[PDB]
Image (cartoon, rainbow over all chains, first blue to last red; front, side, top):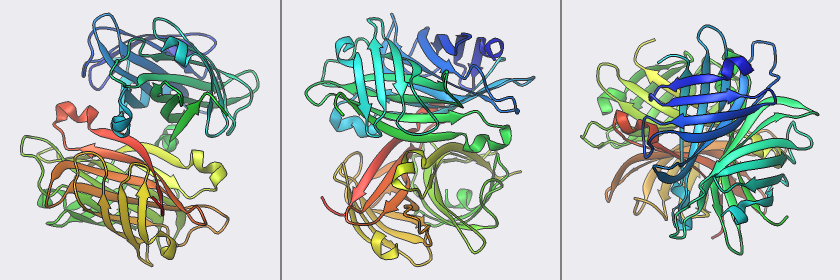
Amino acid sequence: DEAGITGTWYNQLGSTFIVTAGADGALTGTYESAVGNAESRYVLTGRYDSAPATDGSGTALGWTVAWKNNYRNAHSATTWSGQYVGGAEARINTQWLLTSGTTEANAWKSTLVGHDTFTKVK
Amino acid sequence: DEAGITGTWYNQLGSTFIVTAGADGALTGTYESAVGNAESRYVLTGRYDSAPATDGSGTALGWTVAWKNNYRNAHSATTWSGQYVGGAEARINTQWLLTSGTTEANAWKSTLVGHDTFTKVK
Amino acid sequence: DEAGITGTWYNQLGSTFIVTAGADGALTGTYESAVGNAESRYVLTGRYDSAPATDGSGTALGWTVAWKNNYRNAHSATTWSGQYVGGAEARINTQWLLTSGTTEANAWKSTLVGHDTFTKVK
Amino acid sequence: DEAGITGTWYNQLGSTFIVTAGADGALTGTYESAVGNAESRYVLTGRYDSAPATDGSGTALGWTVAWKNNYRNAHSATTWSGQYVGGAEARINTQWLLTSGTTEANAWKSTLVGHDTFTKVK
């Protein structure tokens, strides 16, 4: 699904995810969040299963964005873990973990959890 | 914390995490899991905050492993989200999401969640 | 939101959630899962914020189901954590953690994570 | 494990968890958090597997605390999902989800995730 994953994706928050999938399983691109302490594009890197099951299963993948670029630094990183599903209604369904740099006293409240669904439209 | 993050790390399960941190915020290396449907080394890629807060806070980071290599393919990917804390007892404290490629009927049970703590010893 | 929460709810999987909210913050009822190692109704108990913010915010709540009843025992428990939002399109948006009883060797893969959205219709 | 679960438990943050396990699978008690927007005791309710596997597996359980009592209301609820393990070093290993009441615009950042381990000592 190198061809299927590569391109521009949009989530339910209006965020924009631009990615190139390599033949080996590399994911590389940029992420632009429509919400939060973020502006403009951030580097993303990740991995995907380059030889997925051919029994109608989705393609497992994940990627990371560290929320530092030339404009801002939110001292945090989000990882998305999920699967790509092809076809007419192609989707990337994910759950994510956003961890912020904290003192040891605030480590217990360092990590947000959510879920994003990405589509080729919107 | 380019110097501090780069090197070999070990978690509570006995897994081995070897990483190089770039000046820009890149993480690159290999992961070897002591448990599960895995054998030998897998490529990992990630991001970290290359200019963290200097108020005693940890350094936010994340990385992904797709569980395909030359030996096995478990049709899944794990992302670790957490923070690096330096000093005598240097640690990377993480929470992770392991997503497997599934049919749409089994998507509800596609994602495991856990937490790993990595140290420079063990 | 004692009145608003009390009643029958349905999620995206077709599962049925029947609950009574007490004036103090108690949640009590039964849960029927449309998927997984489950059949018929299971006891649920939980808590909700009985005096929520009046600034348009949702009402925080949570509940637990242990997957043992007279028909089956799946040796597991799911907790849903989320918020109730009233109005025309009333919803309970949740994230959940399903933990299974495991040996210490399999504890790392003991917990599934997902998200359910419940509505008054369907 | 009705006998084993019932009593006072302490986590790594110094929080105190007092619970009575019923024969049917009920959990009832009070929770006192050593951290966060909390003071004194809060009602908790939950469920556990009252007939667990006898193959050395842990006992699945979960419970909820809504962070409202006579002293404070933090407009949030935490659910802990995990398993009880008996013996000399008896433990309750959990992962938790803390959801706060939010506006729809802030729903994406409504949920914290963490992990607590409870012991009979400390």
